[PDB]
Image 1 (cartoon, rainbow, N blue to C red):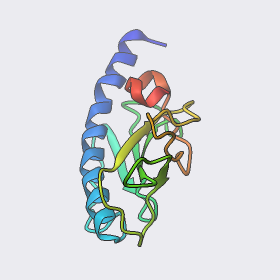
Image 2 (tube, helix red, strand yellow; image 1 turned 30 degrees about the vertical axis):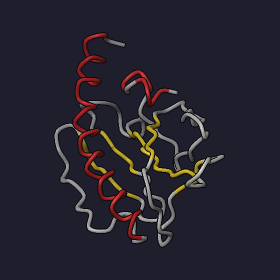
Image 3 (cartoon, rainbow, N blue to C red; image 1 turned 90 degrees about the vertical axis):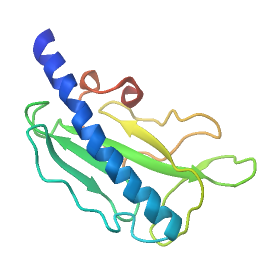
Image 4 (cartoon, helix red, strand yellow; image 1 turned 180 degrees about the vertical axis):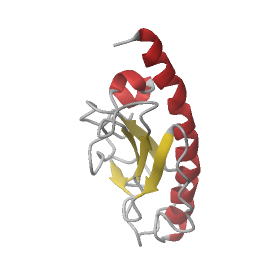
Length: 147
């Protein structure tokens, strides 16, 4: 591809990550209260660079869809996956969020781009995978989304 166009695409991904950070706040609020993980959430209007930022109310997974100013339709999403430790004391695993299950404490987030087929979160271990694989090519994404 074009080095310059690849730079322009990369330079625009942060606007979607910023909208995703607002969505992460909604998920964290609702996780603590046991409510729909998109509770109170207002999905942002489409912009030049970000077509949508959506929350799955059951899992809290966030899908960021970029416009063609970043990448072609169908190869344009990042997925942010939330999780919590299985135990408050000396956990052995991470568990997904689930609507209706109060989840206290710190929520971990993991970003996925295309090609990242396994979680690499640190001990106590892997978090959940995207319900639907991310489709934005890894070359456009931050390092933490590539693997």
